[PDB]
Length: 476
Ligand SMILES: [Zn+2]
Image (cartoon, rainbow, N blue to C red; front, side, top):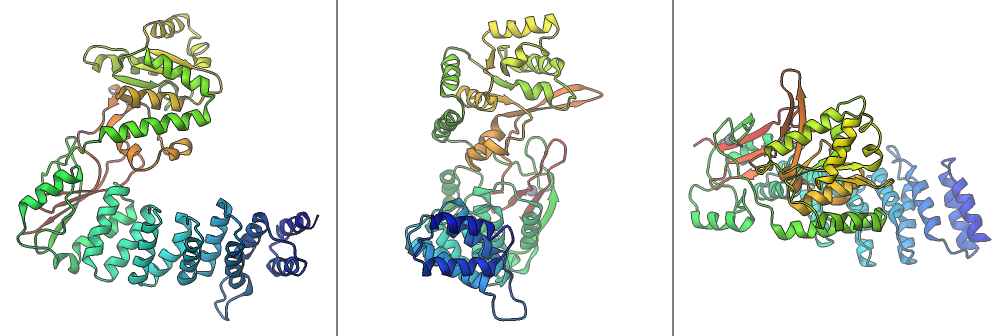
């Protein structure tokens, strides 16, 4: 079969990295009237990615013709799948022509195809590297229109190009986008923001007088912690690296940060999504049986990730650490409720429970309506997540909650819910175990009603390392 033959020959062409032969085989299929499939086109897009940008001649046929092949696949109305977007982007990156990368995205739109975030990258970053803000903002507007949401790298690039071209309005807007979408910024972005606030353009932007009611109504309207009405005040900024104390008080300026509310409607949307995602991955009857059990149990003040409590910082499962965490949670519960312990059934039956009194205790918790043993093959993460969300209560786990399945939960609501609900344990020699409670303020970029800014750096473990903030306050 000829379609099937071209495949074999393109799969073979190549592990070898032979672009000139893939381009020959491409042309031959069209001379033979063999219609290229999704698969053929993808391999061909990949193979062309391997070509390099001619630093000393007119561009090479591999990259150059790669864009041609891309264009033709779309004309042919061959549907793109995830590999198509990836390879198309590699091709764009390798070529490093932002205008040609932008063309590929325009072509996709013209044929009713939704570009991916990675499709926009080579265009956005290309224009930003070249200092072409006007084109960078075109790409940004295109992405907004296609409903593709930027991540921190795209925002930071937009921030820097706005700084480079002295555009104080676009800096403001991008900082608001960082607040809304990212919350806590990387070391790179943090340093960039610090430069912005100490810069001549920042010193020279602002207003001496403004409508206080306008700001007040914007604060209420935006949900808290910002106003979005523009730079306030005048003159040089005092810009310091600082920390918040445990109550959210800036150690530099003594402003107390805001605790920003989560809208209960968002929480109910998230709970529905969580249940849908869990039932796609669990045996549906197993998850449903837990949902039904939970409906008949509680109330709960806390839910414990039993496997994480037994294992975090241990060389093997510590019933001590789990049990001490149960006791601690019950002690801080105003009415002394036992926490809901989520644990695999395997664990309920043999170390923990190697020792008869530990096994009896596990059964006692179950009998108290405070332990659910998840069935073999289940991922218990869905279970403790769903319980904490549904019971609207604390979640005790030191799981990072960022990798694998946790990426499925998104990067707006879930991180905000996490900060309000997650309790983590720490241990010291002098004191033993401690529960680290949610902060009484929101760890996010905040803009105060008088235009003062507080910007938090993102950190891997804010109990291990002390989180740095930027305090930017007008000097007069
Ligand atoms: Zn401050």
